[PDB]
Every structure is written in C-alpha cells, then in structure tokens.
Amino acid sequence: PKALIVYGSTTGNTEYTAETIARELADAGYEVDSRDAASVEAGGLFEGFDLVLLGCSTWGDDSIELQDDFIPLFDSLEETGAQGRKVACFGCGDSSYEYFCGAVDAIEEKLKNLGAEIVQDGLRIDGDPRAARDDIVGWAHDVRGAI
Amino acid sequence: PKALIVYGSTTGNTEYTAETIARELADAGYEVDSRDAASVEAGGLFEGFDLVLLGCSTWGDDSIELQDDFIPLFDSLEETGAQGRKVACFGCGDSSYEYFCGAVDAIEEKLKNLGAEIVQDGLRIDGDPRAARDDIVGWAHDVRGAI
Ligand SMILES: Cc1cc2nc3c(=O)[nH]c(=O)nc-3n(C[C@H](O)[C@H](O)[C@H](O)CO)c2cc1C
Ligand SMILES: Cc1cc2nc3c(=O)[nH]c(=O)nc-3n(C[C@H](O)[C@H](O)[C@H](O)CO)c2cc1C
Image (cartoon, rainbow over all chains, first blue to last red; front, side, top):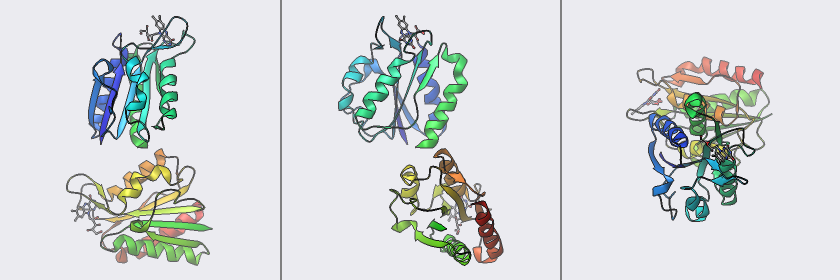
C-alpha cells in the first residue's frame, strides 16, 4: 500500500522517529512518502494514501503549542482528505511538562472530529527517541497489523 | 450454538472442505450458515455468531495472495465484529510452494491483531481434501471442544 508520513521536527527527535517508522513500513512492502511539514500544502495532501501518520512535538510556555512547521497543516486539516482515512499520530515530548505530548492529543482530537479512523493510540516518546527505538519499531508493527 | 463458515474457493477444494466441516457441526446440533465469500458483505457479518470459521486458498506469482473472492472481506475484517469472537481458519494449498497455505497464516494474524480469539490452529490441507477427510473431521471435532 502507500503511506504518507508528515512531521514537524525542531530538534531532530520527531524527524528520527518518523524515519524509523518509515523504514519499518518500507521493509513490510509499503511505498512510503516521508515529508517535513515545512514543505507540504494541506489542500488534498492525503489523497491517494492508504495510511497517513502525523508526528509533532509540543512547545508553549503556558498552553500546548504545536511545532511551528506543523501549525499551518493543523489549521487546514479539514482540506486534507481525512474523512474515512486510516491515520495514527506520534510525537516526542518530555514527561516533566504537564501536558506530555499534548500535540498528539490535539491532532488526534481534530482528526476524530474530521471523521478520520484512528488506527492505534498515539506513540508518545519521552526523552531521546534513540533510547526508545524498540517502542518505535513495536508501534509501527502494530499500526501495520491493524490495517 | 450458531456457526458461520465463510470460504473463498476457486477449484472447489476449499468449498468441499467448508461443506465437510458444516456437516460435522450440523451433526453436533449446531445451526450452521455456510456462505461463499463472493456473496457476502463485511459490515457486521459476524454479529450473532458463536463460532466463525474462515477458509481461503493461497495464490500469487511470488508473493502470497488471497483467493480473489476473499480479498474484499479480508480488507474489511475490522468491520465484521471479530473482536472477542471465537474463530478458526482452514484452507487448501500445495506443499511444493514456498508458503504452504500462506493465506491461513495471513488471516490468523490479522484476526489476532483485531482481538479475535483463535480457538484452534488452522487446518492446512495439502492437495485433494477428499484424501484428507479424516483430518477434516478430526479438526471439526476439535474446534467443538474449544468453544
Ligand atoms: C518551552 C518548551 C515547552 C515545552 N512543552 C512541552 C510540553 O508541553 N509537553 C512535552 O511533552 N514537551 C514539551 N517540551 C519538550 C519539547 O517537546 C522537546 O521534546 C524538547 O525540548 C526537545 O527534546 C517543551 C520544551 C520547551 C523548550
Ligand atoms: C499460480 C499459483 C500459486 C499458488 N500459490 C500457492 C502458495 O503460495 N501456497 C500454497 O499452499 N498453494 C499455492 N497454490 C496452490 C493453490 O492454492 C491451490 O491449492 C491448488 O491449485 C488447488 O487448491 C498456488 C497455485 C497456483 C496455480
């Protein structure tokens, strides 16, 4: 099948995460398209894809603010072709903050409001994702078995 | 009890195996509903059934491919009501191929991932099922004790 991976990454963590999940789907036969959210246009972005995975980090001094490159996509989520789409979300964060991986919850909530089909609960990585490689590959294997 | 048998059969071998099982269960007092996958709709197919038996043959030039009539169902297995359902698989194939009854493995795996309860290891027949009538009968007897 074809999978789209769109990520907003500032420090390289979410990018590394996206890339580890990309390699696992490609190994299972998927044709994978991995894109930085800074370079995509929301209008019809998901058309033609069997599975869409969205990843983003959480920022903000008081509230949950999504990663800067992802904000425009989030704000135009209704024009992407999400209704009825198989999607799953991922993000890196730090459990010391009150809303750990709060960007995953905000994206999952909006996607459910748009009628997307959430295939698996969001992968939330605390600290260095390189330390959690195993959880990352494990979650990729689970989203694949479900669809 | 009520059992549903859904099979994808091209040459008649998976069909004959489905029919032999159906008679064994009917003989043990079950109400059996046997259907060709070509005539079924996936939405809620398993509702109201105590036991669901899925049979499929394996094709494909180099990859393992499901029998054509079963493909649509397999692709929509998440809408059948498999979660918590007691199921078991069966299929005909040929040991000269690299993935002997590979469709049986693919279907068990997906059911597992959907939270179905696999009640007995799948029945894999090499060659003419007419020649393995005893294994068929013995397996149908074994699924009866497990439910
Ligand atoms: C100002 C600021 C706010 C952050 N807010 C959060 C947060 O709300 N939840 C979270 O999981 N991580 C938060 N982080 C961690 C951030 O997503 C990132 O994971 C690390 O700073 C880079 O590894 C924050 C970091 C900064 C600098
Ligand atoms: C082109 C082709 C591919 C087949 N692939 C398989 C396979 O991968 N595994 C298997 O057990 N049988 C395979 N079979 C046998 C097939 O499922 C079938 O059992 C017999 O032709 C009748 O059941 C194949 C048959 C054909 C013609």
